[PDB]
Amino acid sequence: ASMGTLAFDEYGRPFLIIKDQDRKSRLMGLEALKSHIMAAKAVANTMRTSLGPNGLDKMMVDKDGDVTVTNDGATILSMMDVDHQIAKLMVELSKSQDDEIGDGTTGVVVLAGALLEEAEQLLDRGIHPIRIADGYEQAARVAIEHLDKISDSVLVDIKDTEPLIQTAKTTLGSKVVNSCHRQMAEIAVNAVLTVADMERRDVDFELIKVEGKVGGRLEDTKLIKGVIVDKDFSHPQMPKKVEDAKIAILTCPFEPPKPKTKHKLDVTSVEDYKALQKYEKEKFEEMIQQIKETGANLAICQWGFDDEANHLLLQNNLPAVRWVGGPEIELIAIATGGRIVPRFSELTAEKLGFAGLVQEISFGTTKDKMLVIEQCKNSRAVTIFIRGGNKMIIEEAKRSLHDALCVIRNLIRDNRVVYGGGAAEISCALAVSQEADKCPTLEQYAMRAFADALEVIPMALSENSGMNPIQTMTEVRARQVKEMNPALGIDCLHKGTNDMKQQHVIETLIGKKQQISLATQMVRMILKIDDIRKP
Amino acid sequence: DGMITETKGTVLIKTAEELMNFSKGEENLMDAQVKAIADTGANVVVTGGKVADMALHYANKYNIMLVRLNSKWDLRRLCKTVGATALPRLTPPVLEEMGHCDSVYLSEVGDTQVVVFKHEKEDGAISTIVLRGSTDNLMDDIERAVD
Amino acid sequence: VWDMRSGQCVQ
Amino acid sequence: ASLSLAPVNIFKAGADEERAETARLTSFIGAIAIGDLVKSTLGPKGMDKILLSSGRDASLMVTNDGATILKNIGVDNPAAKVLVDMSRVQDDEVGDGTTSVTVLAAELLREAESLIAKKIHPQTIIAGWREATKAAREALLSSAVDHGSDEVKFRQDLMNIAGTTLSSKLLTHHKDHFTKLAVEAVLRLKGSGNLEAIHIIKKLGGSLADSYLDEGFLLDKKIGVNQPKRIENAKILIANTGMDTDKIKIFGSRVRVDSTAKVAEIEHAEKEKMKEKVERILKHGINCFINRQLIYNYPEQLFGAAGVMAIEHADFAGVERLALVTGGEIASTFDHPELVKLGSCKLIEEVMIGEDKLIHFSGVALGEACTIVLRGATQQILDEAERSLHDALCVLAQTVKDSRTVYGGGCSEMLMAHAVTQLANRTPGKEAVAMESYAKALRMLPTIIADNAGYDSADLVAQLRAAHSEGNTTAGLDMREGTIGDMAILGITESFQVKRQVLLSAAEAAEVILRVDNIIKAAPRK
Amino acid sequence: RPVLVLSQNTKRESGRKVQSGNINAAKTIADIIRTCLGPKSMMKMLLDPMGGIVMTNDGNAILREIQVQHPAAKSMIEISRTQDEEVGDGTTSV
Amino acid sequence: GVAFKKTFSYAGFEMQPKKYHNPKIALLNVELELKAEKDNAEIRVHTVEDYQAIVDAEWNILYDKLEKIHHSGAKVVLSKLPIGDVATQYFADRDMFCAGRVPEE
Amino acid sequence: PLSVFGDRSTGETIRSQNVMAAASIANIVKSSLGPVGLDKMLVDDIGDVTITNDGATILKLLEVEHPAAKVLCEL
Amino acid sequence: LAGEGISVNTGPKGVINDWRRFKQLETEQREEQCREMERLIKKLSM
Amino acid sequence: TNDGATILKQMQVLHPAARMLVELSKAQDIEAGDGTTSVVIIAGSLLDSCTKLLQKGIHPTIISESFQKALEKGIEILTDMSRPVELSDRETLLNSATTSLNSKVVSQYSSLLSPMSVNAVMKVIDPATATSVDLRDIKIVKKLGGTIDDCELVEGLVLTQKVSNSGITRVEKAKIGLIQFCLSAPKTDMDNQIVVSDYAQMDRVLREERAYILNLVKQIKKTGCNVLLIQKSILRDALSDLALHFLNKMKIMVIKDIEREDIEFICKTIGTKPVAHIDQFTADMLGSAELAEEVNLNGSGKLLKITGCASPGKTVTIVVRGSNKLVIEEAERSIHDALCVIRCLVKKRALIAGGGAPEIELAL
Ligand SMILES: Nc1ncnc2c1ncn2[C@@H]1O[C@H](COP(=O)(O)OP(=O)(O)O)[C@@H](O)[C@H]1O
Ligand SMILES: Nc1ncnc2c1ncn2[C@@H]1O[C@H](COP(=O)(O)OP(=O)(O)O)[C@@H](O)[C@H]1O
Ligand SMILES: Nc1ncnc2c1ncn2[C@@H]1O[C@H](COP(=O)(O)OP(=O)(O)O)[C@@H](O)[C@H]1O
Ligand SMILES: [Mg+2]
Ligand SMILES: [Mg+2]
Ligand SMILES: [Mg+2]
Ligand SMILES: [Mg+2]
């Protein structure tokens, strides 16, 4: 069942077809499908334990020994060192879900694993895999239509952020920041809403600078309606706090000008040397005077500067910073409402950015100094400063906040939501099963397999919360059938009720639709593969 | 492209005016050269070397077809076919050095893009046989038979 | 690393 | 089916994966090993460890600091790495509490292992620990006492805090003198948190009791050749100029002439420019000149002929410290002498410390920069003394920034543990068991403190628990004889910030490690 | 690892090449003793593997001391032996 | 029409508006950034006035190219060659759009 | 899955292998059929020669490995 | 470093295929070395 | 070697306790300079006693506290046993130096090295007010050849650099000057190039360079300087061929490649103010000396000694000579031990008996 076709002749002479055909394996027919299904099942069963509020974290170690404790499914699978090609396909599935939506990167893996598990027993009964894929696609269309039917709209206005805060809380519940849950959700909602082109357009994440510094406490995480900079004032004797600052943003180093072209300046006499020295001194004084003429109280440079400029700035009561990064320059000028000026001669009063407070922040006994610019008038750029007891919690909070921001961005794109906790999955499974009964017999099996694979998310939630999966799932489904209420889900937090609408477990419709679509397409693609030719 | 000194080229700038006018002067010279070439009626220019960006821009401005041939044998064979002389500099061609061809066009045969210098007359210095086939080895055998 | 004038790592 | 126990192989060569019970076992073993390694260095009777390096240097390091111990060890258990990073971050935030936070996290994880063995879901343990941490934080905050108003009471509190911090370290032999030294050094900062302004100079030879805080400042640089070696009523000019073959910053410039006479004239012009630079510096009316960069032979000769000290190569820290201690301004241009403030001090001279000569500043004007000389019998003793003094200075700076203080000697731990037990006694479910385990770890901390001293720890902890439940909220361990006593009367106090950070960081790291059910290792490079 | 019908060391060849090889081997055997026929024949020196020396111009005596690998030459040597045993003369001629 | 990925924007790019209702597109094969005028070019001066004049000449060359592009009436600027940060900020100040290093196809 | 210590061939692969072995055995002796057939030289790597036309003798002398070819030889 | 009683358990039964694959070649060499032992150094010196 | 600190440093001990003992010897050498062997013996014996103390069930903290109490009592006892000493008592200083030198390899030569060490310490300090001795003011030069009996205390300056000038090896009533610039072709800090566009410019350049060098040498000579020490120069030739030829022609001894680290010592020794530009080179900055000559060490090398000066300010030089390198190194280590003993006597003016008397009294 390998080595291609090992015959070597019909007569006795050499029979060589493919280069190095004696060191190449090959899997054909149903055996390849069984291997792929088993591999995907293993990956999905590994990943399903990190699902829901009661899900447990996974603790990755890379090839350099660095430790990354995380719950993000896409992050977990990305750092996994797999060799099987189907495992790589599942990792890419998670990456696709993270790219398009940013949330639900774990549910897709579990859904694909359940779909392939059902397809295994369907193939065991003699159904062609393409028939299974077609049935899965039909059931996915039915489920997507049902999700659109049972969807609910929310108000995305800035005045009423309660639905947005509830959605962000639902997203963050599974993450470790559920201790600061409400604060993290509120700051994520405010960060997204501040930097967002409000006519239902995109949200640019380059306007959100998520920065984390160790120390402090997780509750100290805050949203700064401005820019926080990892630099400090150039001269140590400059004041540490500037109020009502008028910031001048420059990309010209405070050095005497230098032409780009290959140039030689010839000195031919003592008079020429004196003229050159005087020229340098007057250029320093002239650039400082030009900066001070606009009335700016603070200067920010990108390329650094030398000692004479430093002492002139200190002597003229002009605090300044140097070597600010280009992205940081852009963010500062966006937040302060000022323009970026490439040389001192182009500096005017109208190009100065205004900031209410510019301060230098200390971090205990660590010698590190970081600059913060805030209290702007109408700043269109925000930064998130995360504090924690170790770098692992900093990274985990970073990815959790990214998930929350992505969820609110999806809410910006579309305002339709569905109620999680497995309620949407149970309702979709019920709709799929109902549609199967009104269908010819052959694809009924594929449709019912799709429904059973959909019904794995509530079972995983029940198992992770300690409840009996089958009993709880059956009771919830029976209650959903009895009274028309697709919001009944799995009470993971044991609040006493199954009504997710009353429990405020809210998820975006786009997220569920993308989950189902991606899982269906990848299950079809995996099912269609029947030959493996590893070297 | 504009020819350069064979020994060593160095642009010496001593005033701001020269620096501000050098690129404009080069562009004007290239434009004048290409326009002088085009004013002779030459609507196709074939070169054996590289094509500068400004030269290509000004050839496209005056609606001139450009074809580049790396091999010097190909250039000589094209000169024999059309009846042109390989000029050593970028001067406009004299009445006798400008070859004439009945049709020059870009075409795709199968999956390959080709440039055809087609003569409508049933004569010429050089003739070409285009060989089609389903196998490279088969066409090589057909080429041997043609030889 | 870089900028010996200030004696700090820049960029 | 598992990722590793499957008929198909899904991993690269060398990749590993540990499921629920195996991963929990590895994490708990690593955490307990780290906790048992770092402990026995805790409390007044804690001992030191020797850290032999396996590298080419093979540097020797004896220390009592938990963060130092955890930093310089080869750790491969990832949970142990988490605890090590916790200790490092705790050291960065505040000077003290690394051993306490590491031991607290280890005890919490041991209790978590016991609870898991008792068939309790880890999420229940985490929720119980969250509630317990909230209760303990509230109790510790309520127990805080502030003495920032009264100056003499605050000085007494600072002295007590420095003594408590230095009790465990090697400096406990001369704790009284070292406490006075550290308190004076911190108070000389005039409220600034700049710990870099306090320079520690380690000179071999002499007893540890020979260490002192200089009344002025000490520099480890050299004076020029012909310049004076002693200046009275010095006028200090701190600079950051080149003064080393000072060249015009037009890097495209060059000298292109047609005779050597022109080259000689240009060289004379260069020397004249340097002379004019020195004259402009001298026009300020100074007696001593400190430059961050090097000073070459020509300006040194000019200063010597002018009778002005020229100290060179005082790095950024040096010039900053001189500016803080004398009040001068770090200048780089001298076209406005009247806009530059000049530092001042009563006397500058050269002092003999051991076998090295240092520049001594006496009668400094501002004095907001301390220099401390450490004398020890061995280099290891000097390093440990420097680390202990740094811990004391960090804790004192934190206390100056935030004046709230809490009682030590196990009083705070037992108080928060009593609060946690009170909350657990009125809570239904297994969360009560989890919170009881949290309180048990909190009790275990002073239990380890007493174990390190050899006393009857069980009886002492029982007495402490009885006293804290009865209402005696200031009862703590009296390590002098091995009984319990009043921490307020005895005078064992700690910064509230340090204790709160220890508690919160330990609980957070325990929660982080406890949430893990699977460890996946990628194939290493080696 | 490999699966074969016949053994690994089993080598088979057939066609005009086999006939050419057989005839060439026979011609070589004939050429070995071609010059040892007639009253003017010249003797040959044979070195035994045991160290002995055979100096003769008889066809069978020469051929029986030659070790060959080609089976056609083995057949020709057996022919020489048969002629020597049956009649005792005409060994080179056959 | 045509669509392609964003190509390494420089500082100040986020200031440029990202939607136009009837833009004119300036398709260019031009390097719009400060650089040496030519590979073999060399500047020889002997006076600081000429030094300043040369620096101003380089800046004026760049701004002359940018001003010609602006006066062309275009609102979207596409260049095969890289567009520098100075040109990016110049176009941002005029509510223009720039995108350099666009693939040739 | 099976965890059996050996190789496994299933379906068209093993059938094609069996047919290949049978065809090889047939082609061994196909050239020695009928009056215009010709004999074969067999050498046993020791110097013993067996000139034969009998199919049974040829198939008996040869050492064979594949089971189907062995079946034909015993036939 | 605890848990020295590993009790590898499930490990072998999923890898005995490769273990026996190596063991077969090990034994195959082993007959050769054991056979050559009775001559190579059994009485070479004496 | 017999020095305990050197013995412990040279051998690579691996046990941490041994490393701490090595550090202890280093600290004793820094603070005292003598007793580097006794301190390690004392520490080892204390720890050996600690062994049996621990075996009796005594906590290490109690042992440490009791050891501290015993140390305080011992300090009191030793202070009570000692007697005051005055720096004007030369016989006591000689006795201390001889006692320090008894255990070293130079014990038969102690009659020469004890007064030498006492004088070397005394000349570089002020007996009225000095509270410490800077041993870097005493320069020790190790010259191979001869016997330890040839060790000499030089009052002036001894230079190992050879004289570049040939034919002038003895100057009487010398006027030594330090040069920190270069006597070579003119060269600015900025990149300098001389462009020749005519045939006359070649000889013009040569003539102008010669004139510049000649003017430099003439300005140097006009101040009466007859011995010139040139600082070591890199990136520029310190002494050109023309400069050396002119200086020889005008009867000036030239010694170049003077190390930068020795400039302060030379200035303190011969009273010469260094000059970094020819503009400031005046006769005021010259250091007058009685004699500056180069001597030959009986074929074992050459030395330049400047003995006798107008301002011999707090500096002496000791020339150490011996048959082989090992004995020379041990002799200079022993001389350093003697100097450190006198330095200790200068620091704390207290003398105590030796030969094991303090330890027996302490034990009792
Ligand atoms: N408060 C809650 N109550 C019940 N179910 C929840 C709650 N929060 C999240 N869930 C469920 O947990 C599932 C997993 O969500 P989460 O782990 O946050 O991200 P992912 O979908 O990537 O795993 C979701 O499908 C959701 O239905
Ligand atoms: N004199 C003392 N009496 C009782 N307990 C003390 C005393 N000094 C310190 N401690 C206790 O020792 C514990 C550990 O302190 P230490 O080991 O010095 O630093 P760290 O807090 O980093 O472990 C503190 O929690 C403190 O309560
Ligand atoms: N002439 C002497 N007679 C008796 N004892 C001596 C004499 N000289 C030195 N000692 C003793 O020998 C001991 C060791 O001295 P030495 O070996 O010179 O240096 P260290 O103390 O470093 O070993 C000293 O304690 C001293 O008391
Ligand atoms: Mg989620
Ligand atoms: Mg402490
Ligand atoms: Mg015959
Ligand atoms: Mg001695």
Image (cartoon, coloured by chain):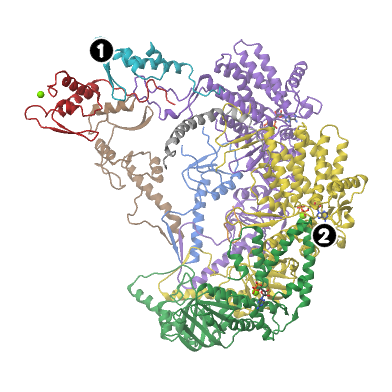
Chain colours: A purple, B brown, C orange, D yellow, E red, F blue, G cyan, I green
Image quadrant containing the N terminus of chain D: top right
- The residue nearer to you, when weighing D391 against I134, is I134
Residue A300: give x, y in percent of width and height. Answer: 64, 55
Q: Which mark is residue D158?
A: 2
Q: Which mark is residue G37?
A: 1
Quarter of image, res D186: bottom right
| Figure quarter occupied by ligand 6 | top left
- The residue nearer to you, when weighing E73 against F59, is E73
Amino acid type assigned to the residue bearing label 1 in the image: Gly
Q: Which mark is residue D243?
A: none
Residue A438: give x, y in percent of width and height. Answer: 65, 11
Name of the residue lying farthest toward the left: E39
* Image vertical order of residue D380 relative to residue B89, above or below: below
Residue A424: give x, y in percent of width and height. Answer: 71, 23
Assess whether mark 1 and mark 2 are in contact (beta carbons under 8 angstroms): no
Q: Is residue I325 left or right of residue G38?
A: right
Secondary structure at numbered mark 2: helix
Amino acid type assigned to the residue bearing label 2 in the image: Leu
